[PDB]
Amino acid sequence: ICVVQDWGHHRCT
Image (tube, rainbow, N blue to C red; front, side, top):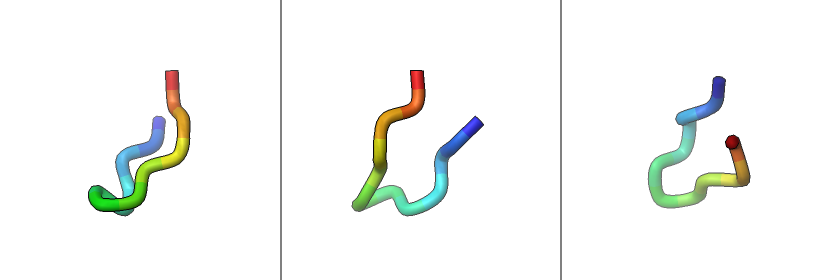
């Protein structure tokens, strides 16, 4: 799970 930083996401699934 990963939804932190809305303006700066990373690469979940």
